DNA sequence: GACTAGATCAGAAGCAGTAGAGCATGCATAGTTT
């Protein structure tokens, strides 16, 4: 049971459920040289904690740091498992060049498929960035949804249907908010379901929803005449039926 | 809401795998 | 003061010590642990040869030679190290408190007599000479035994016996919900009951602030570099001792270790013949020096004998007015000369008379100084130094002589000739205003060596495996912002009055 | 003997270095 | 829900852009 | 007598401080070659 053959390892792990002595004894009984400090001959240093020594090693680009999990997996399978950015904390320039070929800059590969857990691991490394703006992200999402026959999602079923609600007594006035009970929550649900709700009636509006107040129908019918594109007036049964059936209903039956 | 995230993950997986398969095919062609 | 200082940290493990009055506050137990850790680090940096111990009382388990109940000696008297600090670190937090409770326990009874007996037994075990014996009591219970009076009497008797033995007792009383009162029980146990330490204290003791103040500077006990003879003439001789009140501080010497197992290695130097390969001791080889296109060969013994002038000691030559001495003739750090009556009886009287008369007449004793054998003599001046005390009568300047070295003709270097340009009175006045604006009071201990402090911080971080080293604030860096704010416009006026319009000092 | 260093018996306590403090 | 969806889609677009860059580089190399 | 255990002296080890030499590093200064 000697998988290893004349290989030098340095261990500096601190706070861990598998302290240093057990790993050192295991390495010794696995035919593996153990050293207390790194050197030109050692080909890996293991440390499960971000102490000062690992930071110093990181700042000196001459060695590779590997998490303890790599050696545990090696023990489990009784075979030499190839390294991976998953089992790594830092890479020397040679390992950076090697992994830059078949492993992308993040922790993903383009030669082997991936599963849910692997993709979650890749996403964990990625950090939030704010180089985007709402409208452009929405447009890019729409293009992505259109590209790969990707319009079949139930929660993105209103991506391309912007809806304007008649919850304001005076159009284009934010100070005339009403106290609609059903209308307000219905608009909130529409927004939550992927639809786009705009408080200001602009040229980008596509659909219009009017509650049980029919007095405003004439105003909307007059406004749509000047608009280059005419929107459609629909009743509340349309949205409820669409949500219940999980699929869009024809507006002809609800115009 | 809970099922949304798993749907999105399974959704991204297939397209990423398709792109990786395209990379594999291109590398196989380049093997010549 | 000869020997080592031994200290024992008695920490109460009662329930009342683990309760925090406020959510955002440190429990007494955590404060005691922090104080112990700080003292450990300070001792490691300053006096690594001292002995420390840590003992707990009021616990469920026990560990002691006498096998008493509810007394767990966590660490016996031993030199401090990183291992003990790391061991104590596992009780710092709340999880540390749970670990401590699981390991030993809390809420049990106890007797102070047994605690003092265990402390005395620990003191007796040490084989080294102990100049100081000290115990510190970290507790917040002014009435440890209120129900029983026999236990209190036994504790009082044991404390008195320890005091007679020569063991100092200190009480680092901690915060109490009601208020600590020393007058109840601890007036007798404590070695010294200060007059001010009789009121009810509503806050932790002020000594904890001193304990938490880390000292990262080495402490050296008094020692005499040499014990020489002052010879007024061939037949009048007195005995004096030389000390170095100022000495440069250097980093501890590095040690060579093996890479594989960190095992210390030994370094050996040898000299061998090129044409023969044999090993030559440092007596076969000769010495050479090429002067006048010729080689001069001298043996090692002769080379050493070249430096023999006179026997070690100080030889009197005369007395010189202090005015002739020059401040800019500094050559070497000065030394301190004090009487030494052990070698010669009557030295102190003559030394005192000489000091008094030198102070009266404002003169310095010119002498020829030879510290060790086979060392060329030097010319030194002994300047009288009177005894100066501060407000609290603590001596700040000892009485004796200040030995200052005097340069030879070879120690001076010629200077390039430079024409003298005198500034006008207005420029001198503006510079005087600037100087007055930038005035401050100077003290000899107002600065610290950044290199040594950073080295100590890095060493501690490496030993204790801390996340990041502690950064030391440098007090020697000029305060540019404060100086700019204070000076105001004076700099501009001075520059306009002293520099042409186009000068560009930087270029 | 006020001012004695608790940590190191027999040595006078040293105040923390204050650097430069302008009047 | 909106925050979760936007975050996931941003991560996915970044990863897909990296994959497409790799594909383009491989195609350019194969052009030789 | 013998053993065991206390107390006394003298030499060796540790440590501090000094001096000498070498190395390396950096920088400046002046002479020689093209």
Image (cartoon, coloured by chain):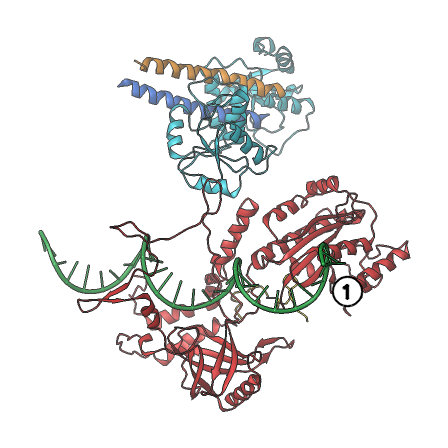
Chain colours: A cyan, B orange, C red, D yellow, E blue, F green
| Quarter of the figure with residue C98 | top right
Residue C94 is situated, as x and y percent measured from the top left of the image, at: 70, 42
Q: Chain of mark 1?
A: C
Q: Nearer the viewer, residue C51 or C186?
A: C51
Residue shown at 66%/29% (left/top)? Answer: A178
Residue labelled with disc 1: C163
Is D16 on the left-hand or right-hand side of A105? right
**Residue A32 drawn at (x, y percent):** 48, 30
Q: Give how far across and how far down residue C174 sits, in percent.
A: 75, 56
Instruction: Say above or below: A176 vs C230.
Output: above
| Camera-side residue of E2 and C166 | C166
Report which quarter residue C501 is drawn in.
Answer: bottom left
- Quarter of the figure with the N terminus of chain C: bottom right
- Give me the residue at 60% from left, 8% from top: A253
Q: Is residue F26 left or right of residue A233?
A: left
Q: Under tag 1, what secondary structure?
A: helix
Q: Is residue A186 visible?
A: yes
Residue drawn at the location 62% of the way across and 34% of the way down: A175
Q: Position of residue C167 (x, y in %)?
A: 73, 63
Q: Give left or right: position of C210 versus C219.
A: right
User: In which quadrant is the C terminus of chain C drawn?
Assistant: bottom left
**Can see residue A202?**
no
Left or right of residue A165: residue C480: left
Mark 1 crowd level (few <14, some 14–19, many ≥20, 10 Å Cα): some
Q: How many marks?
A: 1
Residue A13: image quadrant is: top right
């Amino acid at each position: 049971s000697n998988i290893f053959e004349d290989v030098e390892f340095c261990v500096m792990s601190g706070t861990d459920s598998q302290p240093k002595p057990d790993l050192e004894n295991r390495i010794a009984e696995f035919g593996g040289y153990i050293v207390q400090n790194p050197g030109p001959d050692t080909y890996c240093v293991i440390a499960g904690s971000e102490n000062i020594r690992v930071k110093n090693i990181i700042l000196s680009n001459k060695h590779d740091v590997v998490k303890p999990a790599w050696l545990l997996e090696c023990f489990k399978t009784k075979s030499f498992v190839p390294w991976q950015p998953r089992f790594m904390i830092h890479m020397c320039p040679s390992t950076k060049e090697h992994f830059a070929r078949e492993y992308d800059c993040y922790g993903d590969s383009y030669f082997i498929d991936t599963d849910l857990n692997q993709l979650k691991e890749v996403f964990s490394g990625i950090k939030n960035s704010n180089e985007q703006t709402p409208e452009e992200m929405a447009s890019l999402i729409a293009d992505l949804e259109y590209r790969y026959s990707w319009d079949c999602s139930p929660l993105s079923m209103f991506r391309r249907h912007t809806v304007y609600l008649d919850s304001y007594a005076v159009i284009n006035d934010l100070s005339t908010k009403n106290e609609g009970t059903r209308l307000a929550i219905k608009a909130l649900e529409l927004r939550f379901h992927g639809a786009k709700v705009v408080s200001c009636l602009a040229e980008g509006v596509s659909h219009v929803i009017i509650g049980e107040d029919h007095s405003r129908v004439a105003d909307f019918k007059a406004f749509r005449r000047t608009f280059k594109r005419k929107f459609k007036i629909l009743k509340e049964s349309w949205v409820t039926d669409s949500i219940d059936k999980c699929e869009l209903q024809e507006e002809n039956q609800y115009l | 809401k809970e099922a949304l995230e798993t749907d999105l993950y399974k959704r991204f997986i297939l397209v990423l795998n398709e792109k990786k398969t395209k990379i594999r095919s291109l590398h196989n062609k380049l093997l010549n | 003061y000869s020997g080592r200082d031994s200290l024992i940290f008695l920490v109460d493990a009662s329930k009342a010590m683990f309760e925090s009055q406020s959510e955002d506050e440190l429990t007494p137990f955590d404060m005691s642990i922090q104080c112990i850790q700080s003292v450990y680090i300070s001792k490691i940096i300053s006096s690594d040869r001292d002995l420390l111990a840590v003992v707990f009382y009021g616990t469920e388990k026990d560990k002691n030679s006498v096998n008493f109940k509810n007394i767990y000696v966590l660490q016996e008297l031993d030199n401090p190290g990183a291992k003990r600090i790391l061991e104590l670190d596992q009780f710092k937090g709340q999880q540390g408190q749970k670990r401590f409770q699981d390991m030993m326990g809390h809420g049990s009874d106890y007797s102070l007599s047994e605690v003092l007996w265990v402390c005395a037994n620990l003191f007796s075990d040490v084989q080294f000479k102990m100049s100081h014996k000290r115990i510190m009591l970290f507790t917040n219970e002014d009435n440890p035994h209120g129900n029983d009076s026999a236990k209190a009497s036994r504790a009082r008797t044991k404390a008195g016996d320890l005091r007679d033995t020569g063991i100092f007792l200190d009480l680092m009383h901690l915060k109490k919900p009601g208020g600590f009162d020393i007058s109840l029980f601890y007036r007798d146990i404590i070695s010294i009951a200060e007059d001010e330490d009789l009121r009810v204290h509503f806050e932790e003791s002020s000594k904890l602030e001193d304990l938490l103040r880390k000292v990262r500077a080495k402490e050296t006990r008094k020692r005499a570099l040499s014990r020489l003879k002052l010879k007024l003439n061939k037949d009048i001789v007195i005995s004096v001792g030389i000390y170095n009140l100022v000495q440069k501080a250097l980093k501890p010497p590095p040690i060579k270790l093996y890479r594989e197992t960190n095992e210390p290695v030994k370094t050996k130097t040898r000299t061998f013949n090129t044409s023969t390969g044999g090993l030559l001791l440092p007596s076969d080889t000769k010495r050479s020096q090429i002067y006048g296109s010729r080689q001069i060969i001298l043996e090692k013994e002769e080379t050493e004998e070249l430096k023999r002038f006179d026997d070690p000691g100080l030889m009197l030559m005369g007395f010189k007015p202090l005015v002739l001495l020059k401040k800019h003739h500094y050559l070497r750090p000065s030394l301190f000369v004090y009487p030494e009556e052990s070698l010669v009886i009557g030295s102190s009287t003559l030394f005192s008379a000489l000091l008094i008369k030198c102070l009266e007449k404002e003169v310095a004793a010119l002498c020829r100084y030879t510290p060790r054998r086979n060392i060329p003599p030097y010319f030194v001046a002994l300047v009288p130094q009177e005894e100066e005390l501060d407000d609290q009568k603590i001596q700040v300047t000892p009485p004796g002589f200040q030995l200052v070295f005097l340069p030879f003709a070879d120690d001076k270097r010629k200077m390039p000739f430079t024409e003298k340009i005198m500034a006008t009175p207005e420029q001198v006045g503006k510079m005087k205003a600037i100087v007055e604006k930038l005035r401050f009071t100077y003290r000899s201990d107002s600065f610290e060596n950044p290199v040594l402090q950073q080295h100590f911080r890095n060493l501690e971080a490496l030993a204790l495996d801390l996340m990041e080293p502690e950064q030391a604030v440098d007090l020697t860096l000029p305060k540019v912002e404060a100086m700019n704010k204070r000076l105001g416009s004076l700099v501009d006026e001075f520059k306009e009055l002293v520099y042409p319009p186009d000068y560009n000092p930087e270029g | 003997c006020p001012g004695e260093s608790l940590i190191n018996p027999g040595f006078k306590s040293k105040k923390p270095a204050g650097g430069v403090d302008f009047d």
